Amino acid sequence: LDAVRKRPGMYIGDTDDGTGLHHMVFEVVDNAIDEALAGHCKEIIVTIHADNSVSVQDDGRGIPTGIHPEEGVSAAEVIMTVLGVGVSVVNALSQKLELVIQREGKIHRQIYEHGVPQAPLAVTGETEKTGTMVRFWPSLETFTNVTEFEYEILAKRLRELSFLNSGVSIRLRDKRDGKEDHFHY
Ligand SMILES: Nc1nc2ccccc2[nH]1
Ligand SMILES: N#Cc1ccccc1O
Protein backbone atom coordinates (compact mmCIF):
# COMPACT_ATOMS: atom_id res chain seq x y z
CA LEU A 1 0.00 0.00 0.00
CA ASP A 2 2.95 2.49 0.20
CA ALA A 3 2.55 3.15 -3.57
CA VAL A 4 -0.99 4.43 -2.87
CA ARG A 5 0.05 6.47 0.15
CA LYS A 6 2.80 8.10 -1.98
CA ARG A 7 0.41 9.47 -4.64
CA PRO A 8 -3.19 9.10 -3.39
CA GLY A 9 -4.60 11.29 -6.21
CA MET A 10 -3.33 8.92 -8.90
CA TYR A 11 -5.41 6.07 -7.37
CA ILE A 12 -8.54 7.69 -5.89
CA GLY A 13 -8.82 11.01 -7.78
CA ASP A 14 -8.39 14.65 -6.71
CA THR A 15 -7.90 14.87 -2.92
CA ASP A 16 -8.80 18.60 -2.62
CA ASP A 17 -12.08 19.18 -4.59
CA GLY A 18 -14.18 16.28 -3.20
CA THR A 19 -13.68 13.94 -6.19
CA GLY A 20 -11.40 11.46 -4.43
CA LEU A 21 -13.37 11.67 -1.17
CA HIS A 22 -16.56 10.55 -2.87
CA HIS A 23 -14.77 7.94 -5.02
CA MET A 24 -13.84 6.25 -1.69
CA VAL A 25 -17.53 5.45 -1.18
CA PHE A 26 -18.06 4.34 -4.78
CA GLU A 27 -15.17 1.86 -4.62
CA VAL A 28 -16.62 0.21 -1.51
CA VAL A 29 -20.11 0.20 -3.04
CA ASP A 30 -18.73 -1.60 -6.14
CA ASN A 31 -17.58 -4.48 -3.95
CA ALA A 32 -20.82 -4.46 -1.91
CA ILE A 33 -22.92 -4.70 -5.10
CA ASP A 34 -20.93 -7.75 -6.27
CA GLU A 35 -21.58 -9.35 -2.86
CA ALA A 36 -25.29 -8.53 -2.87
CA LEU A 37 -25.64 -9.99 -6.42
CA ALA A 38 -24.42 -13.42 -5.19
CA GLY A 39 -27.07 -13.67 -2.37
CA HIS A 40 -30.86 -13.94 -2.08
CA CYS A 41 -32.14 -10.60 -0.68
CA LYS A 42 -29.87 -8.34 -2.82
CA GLU A 43 -29.72 -5.16 -0.69
CA ILE A 44 -27.00 -2.65 0.21
CA ILE A 45 -27.24 0.14 2.80
CA VAL A 46 -24.99 3.19 2.55
CA THR A 47 -24.95 5.39 5.65
CA ILE A 48 -23.35 8.81 6.17
CA HIS A 49 -22.65 9.03 9.91
CA ALA A 50 -22.63 12.23 11.98
CA ASP A 51 -18.83 11.99 12.49
CA ASN A 52 -18.19 12.13 8.71
CA SER A 53 -17.57 8.37 8.25
CA VAL A 54 -19.48 6.18 5.80
CA SER A 55 -20.61 2.59 6.20
CA VAL A 56 -21.62 0.19 3.46
CA GLN A 57 -23.53 -2.97 4.45
CA ASP A 58 -24.41 -5.88 2.16
CA ASP A 59 -26.49 -9.01 2.77
CA GLY A 60 -24.26 -11.28 0.65
CA ARG A 61 -22.51 -14.49 1.68
CA GLY A 62 -19.75 -12.67 3.64
CA ILE A 63 -16.29 -12.30 2.14
CA PRO A 64 -14.00 -15.31 2.75
CA THR A 65 -12.36 -15.50 6.19
CA GLY A 66 -10.00 -18.50 5.86
CA ILE A 67 -6.22 -18.12 5.68
CA HIS A 68 -4.85 -17.31 2.21
CA PRO A 69 -2.27 -20.12 1.67
CA GLU A 70 0.18 -17.77 -0.17
CA GLU A 71 -0.18 -14.57 1.94
CA GLY A 72 -0.49 -16.34 5.33
CA VAL A 73 -3.31 -14.08 6.61
CA SER A 74 -7.10 -14.13 6.31
CA ALA A 75 -8.44 -13.81 2.74
CA ALA A 76 -10.42 -10.79 4.00
CA GLU A 77 -7.17 -9.08 5.05
CA VAL A 78 -5.66 -9.86 1.62
CA ILE A 79 -8.63 -8.06 -0.03
CA MET A 80 -8.14 -5.10 2.33
CA THR A 81 -4.30 -4.77 2.00
CA VAL A 82 -3.05 -6.05 -1.42
CA LEU A 83 -3.43 -4.06 -4.68
CA GLY A 84 -11.67 -0.55 -10.20
CA VAL A 85 -8.64 0.38 -8.06
CA GLY A 86 -9.86 -1.94 -5.24
CA VAL A 87 -10.92 -1.39 -1.63
CA SER A 88 -7.29 -1.70 -0.53
CA VAL A 89 -6.91 1.89 -1.82
CA VAL A 90 -9.83 3.02 0.36
CA ASN A 91 -8.24 1.25 3.33
CA ALA A 92 -4.81 2.86 2.75
CA LEU A 93 -6.47 6.32 2.66
CA SER A 94 -8.71 5.87 5.73
CA GLN A 95 -7.48 6.94 9.17
CA LYS A 96 -9.74 4.15 10.51
CA LEU A 97 -11.63 1.30 8.85
CA GLU A 98 -13.82 -1.29 10.58
CA LEU A 99 -14.62 -4.58 8.83
CA VAL A 100 -17.46 -6.91 10.01
CA ILE A 101 -18.07 -10.22 8.23
CA GLN A 102 -21.00 -12.53 8.99
CA ARG A 103 -20.35 -15.96 7.50
CA GLU A 104 -20.70 -19.68 8.36
CA GLY A 105 -22.51 -18.89 11.62
CA LYS A 106 -19.84 -16.49 12.97
CA ILE A 107 -19.25 -12.74 13.28
CA HIS A 108 -15.71 -11.67 12.39
CA ARG A 109 -14.22 -8.23 13.09
CA GLN A 110 -11.08 -6.33 12.20
CA ILE A 111 -9.87 -2.75 12.58
CA TYR A 112 -7.39 -0.96 10.35
CA GLU A 113 -5.72 2.43 10.78
CA HIS A 114 -4.23 3.96 7.62
CA GLY A 115 -4.39 0.48 6.06
CA VAL A 116 -2.52 -1.23 8.90
CA PRO A 117 -4.44 -4.08 10.60
CA GLN A 118 -4.55 -3.57 14.38
CA ALA A 119 -4.99 -7.31 14.97
CA PRO A 120 -5.79 -10.40 12.85
CA LEU A 121 -9.38 -10.97 11.69
CA ALA A 122 -11.06 -12.45 14.76
CA VAL A 123 -14.26 -14.33 15.53
CA THR A 124 -16.27 -12.24 18.02
CA GLY A 125 -19.63 -14.06 18.17
CA GLU A 126 -22.32 -16.19 16.56
CA THR A 127 -24.96 -15.14 14.05
CA GLU A 128 -27.70 -16.55 11.81
CA LYS A 129 -27.12 -13.72 9.27
CA THR A 130 -24.64 -13.36 6.41
CA GLY A 131 -23.01 -10.28 4.90
CA THR A 132 -20.14 -7.81 4.95
CA MET A 133 -20.02 -4.35 6.50
CA VAL A 134 -17.25 -1.77 6.16
CA ARG A 135 -17.22 1.60 7.96
CA PHE A 136 -14.43 4.00 7.08
CA TRP A 137 -13.16 7.38 8.26
CA PRO A 138 -11.38 9.18 5.37
CA SER A 139 -7.91 10.38 6.36
CA LEU A 140 -7.92 14.16 6.94
CA GLU A 141 -4.16 14.03 6.29
CA THR A 142 -5.01 13.10 2.67
CA PHE A 143 -8.40 14.73 1.99
CA THR A 144 -8.32 18.53 2.28
CA ASN A 145 -10.74 21.44 1.74
CA VAL A 146 -13.80 19.25 0.97
CA THR A 147 -13.73 16.87 3.95
CA GLU A 148 -17.50 16.30 4.38
CA PHE A 149 -19.71 14.02 2.28
CA GLU A 150 -22.31 15.67 0.05
CA TYR A 151 -25.50 13.57 0.07
CA GLU A 152 -26.48 14.60 -3.49
CA ILE A 153 -23.19 13.36 -5.00
CA LEU A 154 -23.66 9.94 -3.40
CA ALA A 155 -27.37 9.79 -4.34
CA LYS A 156 -26.67 10.65 -7.99
CA ARG A 157 -24.21 7.76 -8.40
CA LEU A 158 -26.24 5.23 -6.42
CA ARG A 159 -29.28 6.03 -8.62
CA GLU A 160 -27.21 5.30 -11.77
CA LEU A 161 -26.01 2.03 -10.18
CA SER A 162 -29.58 0.95 -9.30
CA PHE A 163 -30.60 1.02 -12.99
CA LEU A 164 -27.51 -0.87 -14.10
CA ASN A 165 -27.81 -3.38 -11.24
CA SER A 166 -31.53 -3.80 -11.53
CA GLY A 167 -32.97 -5.98 -8.77
CA VAL A 168 -30.33 -4.81 -6.26
CA SER A 169 -31.89 -2.61 -3.59
CA ILE A 170 -29.79 0.43 -2.57
CA ARG A 171 -30.67 2.39 0.56
CA LEU A 172 -28.94 5.72 1.31
CA ARG A 173 -29.23 7.21 4.82
CA ASP A 174 -27.83 10.50 6.17
CA LYS A 175 -27.66 10.52 9.97
CA ARG A 176 -26.63 14.22 10.01
CA ASP A 177 -30.05 15.54 8.86
CA GLY A 178 -32.24 12.39 8.54
CA LYS A 179 -32.39 12.43 4.71
CA GLU A 180 -32.94 9.05 3.04
CA ASP A 181 -33.52 7.40 -0.32
CA HIS A 182 -34.36 3.97 -1.64
CA PHE A 183 -33.13 3.17 -5.15
CA HIS A 184 -34.63 0.03 -6.62
CA TYR A 185 -35.48 -0.59 -10.31
N1 LIG B 1 -1.28 9.35 11.27
C1 LIG B 1 -0.81 8.36 10.51
N2 LIG B 1 -0.70 8.48 9.15
C2 LIG B 1 -0.19 7.29 8.68
C3 LIG B 1 0.14 6.86 7.41
C4 LIG B 1 0.65 5.57 7.26
C5 LIG B 1 0.81 4.75 8.37
C6 LIG B 1 0.48 5.19 9.64
C7 LIG B 1 -0.02 6.48 9.80
N3 LIG B 1 -0.41 7.16 10.95
N1 LIG C 1 -18.43 -2.90 2.18
C1 LIG C 1 -17.82 -3.71 1.65
C2 LIG C 1 -17.01 -4.70 0.99
C3 LIG C 1 -17.58 -5.88 0.51
C4 LIG C 1 -16.78 -6.86 -0.05
C5 LIG C 1 -15.41 -6.67 -0.13
C6 LIG C 1 -14.83 -5.50 0.33
C7 LIG C 1 -15.62 -4.50 0.88
O1 LIG C 1 -15.07 -3.31 1.26
Image: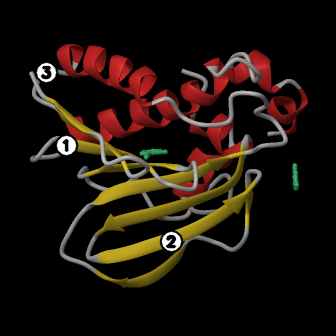
Q: Quadrant of residue 145?
A: top right
Residue 48 visible in image: yes
Image position of 179 (left or right of 91) = left
Give how far apart the Cα atoms at labels 2 and 3 are: 30 Å
Circle number at residue 166: 3
- Numbered label tally: 3
Q: Which residue is mark 2?
A: 109
Q: Quadrant of residue 161?
A: top left
Task: Say which element carries label 2.
Answer: strand
Residue occupying image coordinates x 79% and y 26%: 8
- The percent position of residue 63, horizontal first and vertical second, equals 40, 53
Mark 2 vs mark 1, foreground winner is 1
Q: Which residue is mark 1?
A: 43
Image position of 112 (left or right of 62) = right
The type of residue carrying mark 3 is Ser
Task: Say which element carries label 3.
Answer: loop
- The percent position of residue 84, horizontal first and vertical second, equals 54, 21
Q: Are marks 2 and 1 in contact (CB under 8 Å)?
A: no
The type of residue carrying mark 2 is Arg
Of the pair 83 and 24, the residue shown nearer to us: 24
Residue occupying image coordinates x 56% and y 25%: 23
- List the single residue furthest toward the bottom: 125
Give how far apart the Cα atoms at labels 1 and 3 are: 11 Å
